[PDB]
Image (cartoon, rainbow over all chains, first blue to last red; front, top):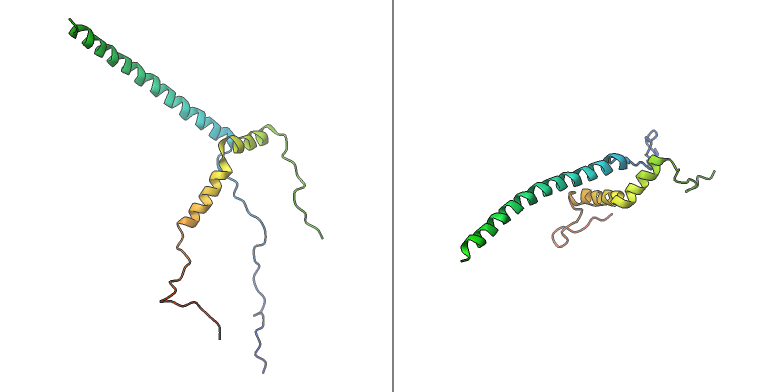
Length: 68
Length: 59
């Protein structure tokens, strides 16, 4: 008999080509969400600094009424 | 038969140029490379402890 190592009846195909999923929410939508999150941070910054100026005027009233 | 590389230009469609400019100004495919190497971070490492497990051989 013959007992080499033969290819056993043919072998299935091996993938042989590039494959790129290329996703990632192309520049329109992600550009938009970047500017939108930036605007959200701006508006919260505006509100908090106005409240902070209120508090700073109260501390000014403290130093004024203390002084004499 | 010859299957050659890079005979193509980035076409001047507005969506093509804004996606390439978003690649530039927002470092996107760089972050895709970061995601690739983190995918190899969470793998199980292919090492062998030598002085207790010697490496494989042949007859």
